[PDB]
Image (cartoon, rainbow, N blue to C red):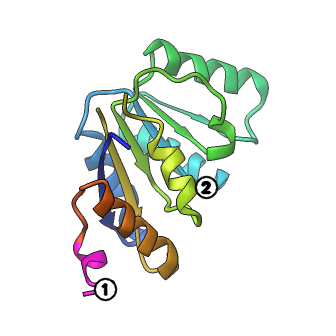
Amino acid sequence: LDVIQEVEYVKEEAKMVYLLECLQKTPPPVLIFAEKKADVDAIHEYLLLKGVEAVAIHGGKDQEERTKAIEAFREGKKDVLVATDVASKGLDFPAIQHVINYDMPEEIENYVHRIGRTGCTGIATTFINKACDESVLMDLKALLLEAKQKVPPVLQVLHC
């Protein structure tokens, strides 16, 4: 409820580059969420290739890896944790300065929970595009407005 939500239209083929730029709105720590394992893996490899202290958690990591990352992050030894929703559930995270939603969830319920991982202020960035159904976009729109947040142009048309 008390986070600055920054929702932005980003073509699928442009997110990786934009993500790098995003990391800079904020000092660490940063949590990047994506629905799929493949994605979490891509983003982590990209961040590494660009030189970001980045760790990743998902259902396909073994116990060694999960533990090592959940805790380097939790100590501040790593700036960025990239996670799936399901892998991050119940983890004890520190004060997160910035949530980056690389995906828009299908349910608005889930958008909230993700952005609910920063606050108590902080920034939530959410990449939206063509693939989102109208319904979630309306609920995102409805939410930004109730939250008294910037509505990006692409949503400002939804209902004029």
- Up-down: is 57 above or below 11? above
Q: Is residue 63 found left or right of 95 in the rendered image?
A: right
Give 55 or 6, whichever is nearer the viewer.
6
Q: Residue at x 21, y 60 (%)?
A: 150
- Specify the amino acid type for callout 1: His
- Specify the amino acid type for callout 2: Glu
Rendering coords of residue 68 (x, y %)? 63, 18
Rendering coords of residue 144 (x, y %)? 32, 60
Circle 2/circle 1 CB separation < 8 Å: no
Question: What residue does disc 1 label?
Answer: 159
* Residue 11 shows in the view: yes
Find the residue positioned furthest to the front. Answer: 146
- Up-down: is 132 above or below 2? below
Find the residue positioned furthest to the top. Answer: 75
- Up-down: is 79 above or below 3? above
Secondary structure state at the residue bearing disc 2: loop
Label 2 environment density (alpha carbons within 10 Å; few <14, some 14–19, many ≥20): some
- Up-down: is 114 above or below 131? above
Rendering coords of residue 149 (x, y %)? 24, 56
Secondary structure state at the residue bearing disc 1: loop
Q: Residue at x 57, y 48 (%)?
A: 40
Rendering coords of residue 37 (x, y %)? 66, 51
Query: Disc 2 versus disc 1: distance between alpha carbons?
Result: 28 Å
Question: What residue does disc 2 label?
Answer: 35
Give 54 or 70, whichever is nearer the viewer.
70
Image quadrant assignment for residue 158: bottom left
Q: Disc 2 or disc 1, which is closer to the eye?
A: 1
Please report the bounds of the magenta region as a residue range: 153-160
The magenta stretch spans residue 75: no
Find the residue positioned furthest to the bottom. Answer: 160
